[PDB]
Amino acid sequence: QPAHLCFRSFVEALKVDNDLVEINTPIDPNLEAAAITRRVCETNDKAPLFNNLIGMKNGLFRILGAPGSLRKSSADRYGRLARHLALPPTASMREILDKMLSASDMPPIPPTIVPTGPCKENSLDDSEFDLTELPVPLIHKSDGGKYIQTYGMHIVQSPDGTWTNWSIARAMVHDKNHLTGLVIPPQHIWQIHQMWKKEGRSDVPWALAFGVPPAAIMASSMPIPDGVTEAGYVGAMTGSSLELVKCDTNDLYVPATSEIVLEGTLSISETGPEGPFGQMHGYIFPGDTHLGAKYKVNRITYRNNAIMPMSSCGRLTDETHTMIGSLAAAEIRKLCQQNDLPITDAFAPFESQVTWVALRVDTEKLRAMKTTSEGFRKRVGDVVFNHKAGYTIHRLVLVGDDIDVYEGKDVLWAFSTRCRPGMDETLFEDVRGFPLIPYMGHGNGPAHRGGKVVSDALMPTEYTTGRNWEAADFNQSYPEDLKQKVLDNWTKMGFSHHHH
Amino acid sequence: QPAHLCFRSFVEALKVDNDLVEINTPIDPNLEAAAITRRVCETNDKAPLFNNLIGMKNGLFRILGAPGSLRKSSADRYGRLARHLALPPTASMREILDKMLSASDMPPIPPTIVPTGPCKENSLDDSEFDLTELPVPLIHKSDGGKYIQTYGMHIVQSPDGTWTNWSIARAMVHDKNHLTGLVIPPQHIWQIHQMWKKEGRSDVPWALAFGVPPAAIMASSMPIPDGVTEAGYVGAMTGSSLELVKCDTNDLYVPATSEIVLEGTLSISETGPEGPFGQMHGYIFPGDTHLGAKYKVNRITYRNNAIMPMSSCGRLTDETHTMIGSLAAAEIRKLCQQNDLPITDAFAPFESQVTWVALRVDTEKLRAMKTTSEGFRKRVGDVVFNHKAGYTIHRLVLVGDDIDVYEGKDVLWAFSTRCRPGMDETLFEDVRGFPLIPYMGHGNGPAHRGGKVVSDALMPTEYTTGRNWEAADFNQSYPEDLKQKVLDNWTKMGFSHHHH
Ligand SMILES: Cc1cc2c3c(c1C)C(C)(C)C[C@@H](CCc1ccccc1)N3c1c(nc(O)[nH]c1=O)N2C[C@H](O)[C@H](O)[C@H](O)COP(=O)(O)O
Ligand SMILES: Cc1cc2c3c(c1C)C(C)(C)C[C@@H](CCc1ccccc1)N3c1c(nc(O)[nH]c1=O)N2C[C@H](O)[C@H](O)[C@H](O)COP(=O)(O)O
Ligand SMILES: [K+]
Ligand SMILES: [K+]
Ligand SMILES: [K+]
Ligand SMILES: [K+]
Ligand SMILES: [Mn+2]
Ligand SMILES: [Mn+2]
């Protein structure tokens, strides 16, 4: 089975890529696995596969850390992401995001139901498992629980059956048969949960699948539109119908090659303690526990020699940056284009802790609009910040055509030199804010509202007659023939490879 | 003569450091020397010494590029700066800035007049030189003139004789015997020029010395206080009186080992076309020529085999960043401390194009002040932005004790995660602005006023009870014994030197 359609095959791809380290000696899930993984993430090392995890019983479980983190080399920097999508490992960010947006004007390819799959190789009923006895990792020393769920896919369906949503949301072990987790607006898991609550008849049928097809975990991390079933979108993007099996205890369908599947319910009435968790902005607030959603687990099914993917998230760079940020940015690009705004490219700079998105403007189109900064800033921010795709993003940086938004140094250059503080900015206080950013939920103002800004790093002539500068750099401040001479004579003169 | 007291010795130090490339084949001063130097600056390579410059006549001149730029290695990153000051080449930025601030509470050590020096080895009177015939570089392709003066020291004295100022300010060749250059408020060259203009009796006696003692060019780049003679300050910092010789045509005194000295006058009445010049923010605005100050050159004196230092300035990283930014930041640190503000450290992040300064706060002292963000922001910004040392700086970022302000990635982390846009900021519109930033002089508002901000990246409990988070990183989210195990087993497990 191809790597993008089967997690087990993905793992093998990473091996073949010389991008895996298999650790076959005992590793403690209490902090050690996550510490190793954190180090990998801070240094762009190879992904760790823990094949000998202290506490693994009856095949539950091995761990793969850093499944969507960065490689060291520039030439295959995003290679692990490319492997989730059948792309060459040298694929650019633009090519990855274009792949993820490609199904947005294609017909969905609905999934295919099959009678069984690897995810049925083993099962544990209500009398045979205990979630407190599994080798669930403690990821950060101050976490409020053992976070089993950092890279699985929650599966919930609208009461009417018409929309089945796949998404990632964190969850931790509460007791032998329950999790607690984040279910917050405007996320689709929350939107669906609200529909069940309003109906008031039953708890929400639920499954959580770990080690799902890599192309599915990437759509899981992406804010595709409301009411769109991720399975169909993945099918369209990959050109193939996903093979799903029915759960044993409910009528939901899980990917046939899922490593591990939990089946049960998301309560419409109960909560339990959840968090804190060391998260995407880089922080843990020890003791900041709050009531979260509560899931009941009725049944576990799993592959032989099951592997649990884990994100040891926090400071740069991990899946919370590479996937959350980039995929939001992709959707924001599309949203802007659909609103007739002249945006060519969007990216969340890692340097911003994925709280900014830089928007590359087609300034020939902008010129034709005959507008102003004030007007244009307002229009862009109203589009993006009133939409779910803008939820995580607190600063939009508008930049002209000379800036590569996929290069943080060039975004910082433009921001610092072209956007006058105050005058070239519009503040948005009456928009939904992202509370998990420290300056929001642990800050000076309302946790859930405002704190957003559009920073205009377009120069004034970009609205009127065209760019009126050249950069004072090697590329722009010297003619071609000279530059090439300089390069050709560089090592001859005594000064100091793409792949590395 | 020691490297910090004699430019020729500095050049030799760079050789011995294996931090020089001597180019003995013909190099064109029309763009080629500057292009090579620009490439060095963008890649942190070795400094270039052009010993064979097309157009050099009668010993005028060789060029040394990138005299204060960065080295490739982390361990001696600031080694060229350290060599200007007799510091070890592994010196930290904090150690360099502390050295530059060290003379601020010491008695000045006034200079010593000597009867001659190397700078008198050769001379050209009013009938023997022509500045248009020298090998003055064209530094960027769109510059408005050939910028002879990018790393020399202007020497002007108050009418009353009490203050002799040393500073760097750009200047370009106007004609055979004149330069034009920037003389702008609040710079000391401008302050002195104004005193002469108000007296109205004569043009300002002037000299411009190139290849001066490296400890003197660093004070030249630093905004020490009004009325303080740089020579005395350099003397105190170095522990030795500087040896100066009298000019031939006026009563000013130049460093005895100056490579090249121009003597003449700065006009109190004439101007001429000046600029554009590819500058510290990274931009040139082709055609943006404005009237500048005009200097008349009466006499040139020079060393045998004279060497002209040159800054090929623009995008990161060159002397405009490493010296302008850092030295301003140093003076801002002191200023804050003298105003009873609990600032421990200041640095201008290169990522900001040296338009920001990050201010590290002693939060135990802050707590004792029993204040608020709003109040504290106002107080800091009133100090800094009403002072000359704050002139170039448009954003102040306040950060707590966990942040190393000398590390741009940590400043960006804190800014992006701890400062709520709008609410955690105070805008300053009634302060002097720095017009050379593009968003000022080529922007939407007044070129000379406002555009400044204090961004408070202190969290709320830093004002009250103490930091209430841990970072979700390897350093803070795992106990010591585990971290050390992980490190000790890193290469055993199969994962991947300070000097590299
Ligand atoms: C890739 C990844 C994604 C998330 C999350 C994680 C990872 C690795 C962690 C490791 C589990 C951390 C945590 C970050 C939390 C976060 C909250 C809200 C938005 C973004 C991030 N997490 C989400 C979490 N979302 C929460 O609501 N809830 C979560 O707990 N996300 C992001 C979430 O998958 C994306 O926003 C999707 O667009 C949601 O899908 P949806 O559009 O609602 O169908
Ligand atoms: C290290 C360096 C320093 C400057 C300058 C340059 C270099 C390499 C360039 C290459 C010549 C570029 C140019 C940058 C311009 C600039 C203007 C005003 C402030 C900062 C920079 N330049 C200055 C220029 N200042 C101008 O007024 N005038 C100038 O032309 N500076 C900075 C200037 O030396 C410092 O502000 C000093 O504090 C001035 O000394 P002072 O306190 O007035 O005794
Ligand atoms: K999704
Ligand atoms: K702007
Ligand atoms: K000075
Ligand atoms: K703050
Ligand atoms: Mn969805
Ligand atoms: Mn001065």
Image (spheres, coloured by chain):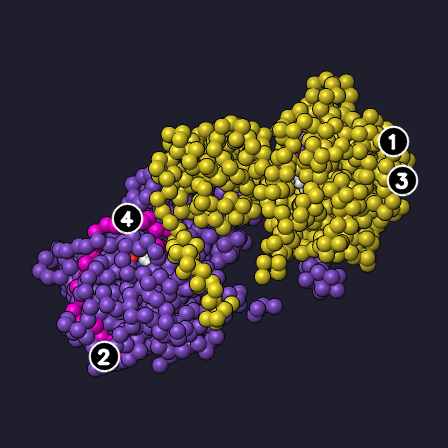
Chain colours: A yellow, B purple
**Vertical side of B306 occupied by B473: above or below:** above
Please give the residue where the numbered disc 4 appears in the rendered image: B288
Circle 2 SS class: strand
Looking at the rendered image, the disc whose residue lies closer to the viewer, 2 or 3, is 2
Circle 3 SS class: strand
Please give the residue where the numbered disc 1 appears in the rendered image: A115
**Residue A86, horizontal then vertical, whole percent:** 70, 43
Number of other residues with Cα within 10 Å of mark 4, as a class: few under 14, some 14 to 19, many 20 or more: some
What is the spatial separation of the Cα atoms under label 2 and label 3, in whole angstroms?
92 Å
Please give the residue where the numbered disc 3 appears in the rendered image: A122
Answer yes or no: disc 4 within 8 Å of ligand 2. no
**Vertical side of B268 occupied by B251: above or below:** below
Give left or right: position of B116 versus B317. left
Three-letter code for the amino acid on which mark 3 is drawn? Asn
Please give the residue where the numbered disc 2 appears in the rendered image: B122
Residue under the point 72% across and 32% down: A235
What is the spatial separation of the Cα atoms under label 1 and label 2, in whole angstroms?
96 Å
Residue under the point 31% across and 55% down: B143
Camera-nearest residue between B194 and A109: A109
